[PDB]
Amino acid sequence: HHWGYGKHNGPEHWHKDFPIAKGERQSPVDIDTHTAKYDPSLKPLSVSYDQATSLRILNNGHAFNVEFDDSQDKAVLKGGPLDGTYRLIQFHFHWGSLDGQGSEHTVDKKKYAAELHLVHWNTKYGDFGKAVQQPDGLAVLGIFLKVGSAKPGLQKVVDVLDSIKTKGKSADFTNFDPRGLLPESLDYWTYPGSLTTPPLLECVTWIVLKEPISVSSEQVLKFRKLNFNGEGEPEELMVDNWRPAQPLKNRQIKASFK
Ligand SMILES: NS(=O)(=O)c1c(F)c(F)c(S(=O)(=O)CCO)c(F)c1F
Ligand SMILES: [Zn+2]
Image: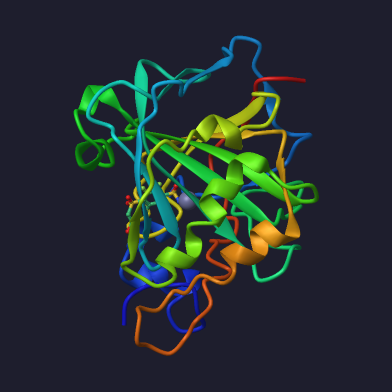
């Protein structure tokens, strides 16, 4: 009876196994745009993905992860609200059963169809497993997805999905360039928060881009054909793998822009 996304083992149950679920800096949150504070001293985000080495794509039973070689500073995030340097380890998405839901963060209560998380760890901690045990261990770049015109840089991911339909499957996934998933603007909101799935650790500097990307209905439909189950088990479509917004508590969301 492990955690997941249902009646029986979804977000409202997680706190029994992972009591920080009710902690002081949980994610995601609703981004009230009018109340976010413009901070003129926030720096532009530096996204340096040119040397990124994707390796593999994995269905982990909760989402799919596109993995990168994080054994050197290739793709890194810095600047923005951060100190030092954060290495890209993986990206994944959260999405809905319907275009009207799927994102984890919300913007003035608006839900997007999906949300991309580019996950980076602070090189001062040496590796990801140590970093998650630190309050400044991770920087997650969140990017909203709306349904409209296709994102051509996404198709390379969508098309491999049938090879990883079920939980535990992986496929080689080299030469994927995550720059093709970015919107034009790097304007952002930022706040201190947590992992949005168990173990829910309070180790994340969240950086959420204001500009969504557009993906097509057909692209997101392919996400919804993935399965939470393993091969040879009853089919449970991988949909609605998002955590709802959590109490903001004693936090201020900062905006890089006005
Ligand atoms: N959605 S999110 O970006 O916050 C995110 C991560 F990026 C992430 F790497 C993990 S994890 O702790 O690696 C494994 C979960 O059991 C997470 F748990 C997790 F929630
Ligand atoms: Zn995520």
